Length: 320
Length: 320
Image 1 (tube, rainbow over the protein chains, first blue to last red):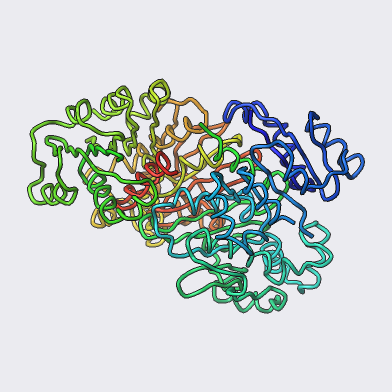
Image 2: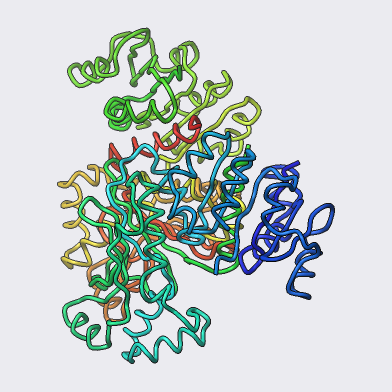
């Protein structure tokens, strides 16, 4: 019996519960029997014997769970084997450290702890006898972490160049097509739900840079946030797309970790290049020494998409 | 001490030895100590204590190895834990079955046994307590098998459409660019070493179809070779590329497994679509239920590239 605690029950955490319910037969015939023994949101929790669909109904119906006990108490006291840490940031680091220090596996979708304390957390997991999985932190459903770390393990990954923010990719693709000012394309992005009222985390390249730090570290390049040169998309105009088009280029926000660079910024990309992908998409080009160049593309976010990444990590920990 | 036998010592097998030598420090600090205890080509072998560089020097210098004992004897009698089966087909099925029946892991690059006896071999591996790895059978260095089978494990992969033959991709890209008859572009392909004197295995779509069968089966679609509708590229002319270009399309040999189809044939692909990739490349688009659409592209063949795939499988069996 695999015992799972879910901490964080906004969009992602609820996504994980939906998927665990929907794919229960397939999950169980792959990793064996499982039960979610605790769920916690930002101010309440449910533990003991309860059903996931109960927890889910209650959260949707009331905006909270059943008990007053906070996420930290569930992390330090509940009976579980693996913690799914999908906490709503806007604490996370402490939930991870405390589950790892209890000798529990951790699957997370939070970038913050990994950006602030990457080697400190990987080592803590190693010192205890457990794993810290983080596929959902970068690329959403797109394999990136397991690809860099498991598939390409005995290769020297020399560089990664990619697109790690769907919202900026959408804004730039849309600006390319419509040729309308940034202010207007942003309002569309907001109407569609891609960008919040304060779209800064996306448009100033912060999200992409956080992800770039996680990737840099995953491939063996020690890096902190302050090491990344970050430039957003707010000064890209339709006129920029026009002058670039005339010479065969589109414009994309590209995150790169190489020997020469560690940056997130707009860049000219030839129309038929793999990184010229449009819409709310992610992409990554890995340049290696023995496997050549390896390219991946997919959805970089979404409820079911993020939930999928979390599940791929749970499978990796327990498949046999 | 992990004991490896290598069977098949043409281009691929020699590639595996080169990589095992070149990446020895990194491999050992990832999976522990290893020694190759036997190597066999199509008519000779070397076993006991010998060095890999000895085996390699001898093969290059003389065209063969040291002992008269054939691959089958090394498979049924040599002391090894994992068999790397890279045999030069133009026997393989028997080397796999006999290593699995001895309770040995098997990593292969041969398509034939998997196409003829997929479920029979997976079950034999399961009945004994071992693994049959086959990343190198399709996509070369490009993750395809571990992607379909490990990353996308708890997803329902609804379809795979890809490009699984670099030579046809090259011939079509080259024909698109130069606009010269098939006979001429094939001669270039031959001069470059991409196609043999008899290029049929490539140009008639046989290679791509074998690979399509492996993939279909990997994703849960029971399929035999006779189930695939196979059409090659020998009747694609420059004029076809011209009429397609006028409407935004290029032409590619696409392998597809879906609910509606199981085929390999030429197909119109929009210029800016991910499967419009040019050169000797591979590519695959996985359409799933929970992770959206996932795309991968890379080198589909080569000595170091195939060797890499084999190593990624060895890592998967023994990383901890």
